[PDB]
Length: 260
Length: 260
Ligand SMILES: O=P(O)(O)OC[C@@H](O)[C@H]1O[C@](O)(COP(=O)(O)O)[C@@H](O)[C@@H]1O
Ligand SMILES: O=P(O)(O)OC[C@@H](O)[C@H]1O[C@](O)(COP(=O)(O)O)[C@@H](O)[C@@H]1O
Ligand SMILES: [Mg+2]
Ligand SMILES: [Mg+2]
Ligand code: NA
Ligand code: NA
Ligand code: NA
Image 1: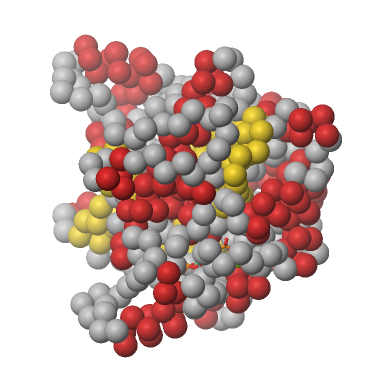
Image 2: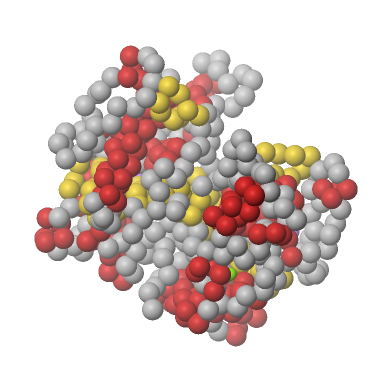
């Protein structure tokens, strides 16, 4: 089977339901968000079989509690045996956009704050181009997500060459995963790794079974990719023509027609 | 509810399963393709409820038999009452890329044919940029798909303003729907309608309840959007922030978490 990257956004939180920007703030899932992530896992493993546990090799997660809680609940339907054959890796490159000054704020409130600081005179604020004051720029996030992508695709290639199926999961956040999905299939711009930041190993994860990939170049966005992904939403990124060098977006998300 | 465009690729055919390019050739579904589209409709309407019939207003279909067969089977689970409240429109702007010389051929055979005609000297053939000899260019397909999109989004806007939910379905083909999805959320390039071809009404459908939208500009691709969509696959295109002017791709395809 063509290897896939299954992306999963953390379930609902107090902020995510009210539209407030959650980055580093370590919010838990609301009680609704736990229920929601439980039913999601039953849907994908049980009532439908969008995911086959035997084919999951790796699960990568943001270190945020809401992401790790989401791994916990979505994987509930698995047996201890299926779990034993799955590796879980906490990766700091998968955290949300660092919002800096905009932590816990709404879009309309961010626009208002920037207006008062004398910004966005010629054109409206666009996070994907502009980033966040005292937070991350679009290249900083595009760089760390590029590193995780290269590790995931290297694993995929290694597994395909060992002749095995490889679904790898990624549990993270609304902005980071939209960004992740966009650059995966080739949106944005290529930049060579030249500066100190672009070239250093930052040691964002610690699992010796995941080879670190030193990038010569990375991708970042300069505009809105125009994606939707709700709390607890599931995307699928794969490859065209069984070829790791042809990374593609799966339009059906996790949906597949039931077998005969 | 935010209006959506649900895209559906025709089920399996003799050519689609063997990789042969099907445009105008009016192939039927294989027996497997019928069963496959029946189970798909049961999945989306019955066993899961990815689609709610009460929210479907319009169904647009390529005139090809395999597309119309696919409408027939996917909508099997509906009652006659639900069907009575749904309008079905055959639209010629939704046909497949006209492959011209490459009808019924494989990719590698197309490459071989072009090589022998002394083409693709500097760079490999790329349908999304180059089109097909004696078939459609990328702007011809980008133009007709732009017209259908404008009609679909106008309907969406009209329905949203009447205060109603609007899922609109589009049954077409592997290339046309990938192309459709790409330009929907803003890939490719904008071109003004200036030439005779770009400006004429071609009368591709006949349903008086669908206002014709005269384009001042249209979008077309110049490269591979890098999408996957299998036979019988389902994509979802919608809008960000309940706003028809913010068209977006739904990364979860038709998947939604089961309700509480
Ligand atoms: O792009 P738009 O739609 O304007 O804004 C959506 C975007 O703001 C969401 O992404 C989040 O990071 C979600 O984070 P989470 O997955 O709960 O950790 C939050 O800051 C937001 O609610
Ligand atoms: O882009 P790649 O993957 O190289 O090629 C896939 C593309 O060639 C398919 O799209 C089709 O039009 C399918 O048409 P259908 O939906 O059955 O009417 C056929 O020409 C092909 O099999
Ligand atoms: Mg949150
Ligand atoms: Mg066919
Ligand atoms: Na919370
Ligand atoms: Na969330
Ligand atoms: Na219309």
